Amino acid sequence: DVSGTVCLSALPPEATDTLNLIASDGPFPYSQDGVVFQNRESVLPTQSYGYYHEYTVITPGARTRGTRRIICGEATQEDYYTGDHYATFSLIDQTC
Amino acid sequence: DVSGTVCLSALPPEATDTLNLIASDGPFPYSQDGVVFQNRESVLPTQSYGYYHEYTVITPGARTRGTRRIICGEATQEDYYTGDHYATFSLIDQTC
Ligand SMILES: Nc1nc2c(ncn2[C@@H]2O[C@H](CO)[C@@H](O)[C@H]2OP(=O)(O)O)c(=O)[nH]1
Ligand SMILES: Nc1nc2c(ncn2[C@@H]2O[C@H](CO)[C@@H](O)[C@H]2OP(=O)(O)O)c(=O)[nH]1
Image (tube, rainbow over all chains, first blue to last red; front, top):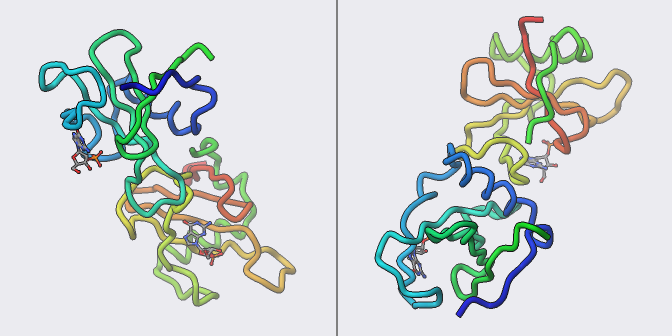
């Protein structure tokens, strides 16, 4: 289930950077940015394989890629944020 | 993010000295010159560990290494100046 919506302005600033890269189709910092997200635990609506893609949301200070990600769906503005490595997802509201 | 491009001629003259040292591979005044800059805060573009190195820019009169540094990247002419101990960065243009 998606856990509600979150205003873009309430997320870490790096969430805004990733959306901007997603919009320009990169270039992305990591070679894993843009891989298909499988939605293997069925948290998001079931769709054909390849409908969802994931992109890193950089966590300043982490020594790795960390756990923040933006998952896009194929619908317009269908962008979900996860700060816990896919345990929970919130639909991003870009207007607040 | 990088704050913009600045002409080397517009930075303190000690920046020029540091770049000259880097071009000849030293010798450097401080033992810390040439250590890896981790880019831990993610202010500069994401790169592998060791792509960036830090060099002191002497602050006239200071008893310590102070807050000025030159960060080099592995790309041709990629050198950044920080006057606030890595809070902000500017790309150095050596052509002006
Ligand atoms: N948990 C989970 N990981 C997925 C899924 N689809 C792709 N992955 C990626 O496969 C890896 C296997 O654990 C995850 O770390 C994640 O890599 P990312 O770190 O790039 O997000 C999915 O549906 N669920
Ligand atoms: N803030 C910051 N310091 C770094 C980084 N990489 C190396 N350092 C150096 O590591 C220290 C301890 O964390 C910092 O005070 C700084 O010491 P210098 O002043 O010698 O560069 C980095 O990526 N960020």
